[PDB]
Amino acid sequence: SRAMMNAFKEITTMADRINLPRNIVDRTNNLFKQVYEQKSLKGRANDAIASACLYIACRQEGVPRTFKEICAVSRISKKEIGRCFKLILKALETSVDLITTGDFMSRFCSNLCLPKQVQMAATHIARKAVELDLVPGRSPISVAAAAIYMASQASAEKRTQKEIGDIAGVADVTIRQSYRLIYPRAPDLFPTDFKFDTPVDKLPQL
């Protein structure tokens, strides 16, 4: 047992750089030990397997912007976390898709001190994203709550998957399946309003 003890130090060191509490460090640790012996993770990326697990326990509630942020905390082969991620996600998808309807108001989506600047900026992204059909996996209203958590990372306004997506009582497959594939290689969905409070000029991924 060696790499196993090395993946536990990368699971707690990653949450310490994401500004998250030990709560996310308790899920990323139990997430790696639960998928550390999978039939596709003999041990070729202890830091890449933990980073993904972090994007899970945090995407549920405790991560601003999106995975693009949970990645800035880890730098172990960014070409693997993407794969190993789909593996730790299949072992625990979610099964929350049971609303995707109580998000048309978009008024209670800013109960965490969020500025309307990102509220009108998010609608602009889902405006051309839903009108162009880039990821109609679930429904259109899903792009509404996914555009709110997507604008938080491009409107110089960071938030949390909880106060940004959980407050929408929509579904985890709406924000994660809305941007999971709503861009070819960047957020080029803005119509012209979203001036891009943040200087990303290329902020893909949610």
Image: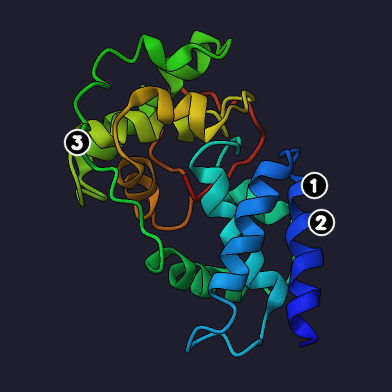
The residue identified by callout 3 is 140
Rounded to the nearest angstrom, the CA distance separating label 2 from label 3 is: 37 Å
- Please indicate, yes or no, whether residue 102 appears anywhere in the rendered image: yes
> Are discs 1 and 2 less than 8 Å apart at CB?
yes
The residue identified by callout 2 is 13
What kind of residue is marked 1?
Answer: Arg
Image position of 132 (left or right of 203)? left
Image position of 19 (left or right of 28)? right
What kind of residue is marked 3?
Answer: Pro
Q: Residue at x 63, y 40 (%)?
A: 200
Select label 1 or label 3 by which is in front.
1
Q: Quadrant of residue 77?
A: bottom right
The residue identified by callout 1 is 17
Rounded to the nearest angstrom, the CA distance separating label 1 from label 2 is: 7 Å
Rounded to the nearest angstrom, the CA distance separating label 1 from label 3 is: 34 Å
**Circle 1 residues within 10 Å: few <14, some 14–19, many ≥20:** few
Q: Secondary structure at mark 2?
A: helix
Q: Residue at x 60, y 36 (%)?
A: 62
Q: Is residue 183 above or below residue 158?
A: below
In terms of depth relative to the viewer, which is nearer, 76 or 34?
Answer: 34
Q: Secondary structure at mark 3?
A: helix
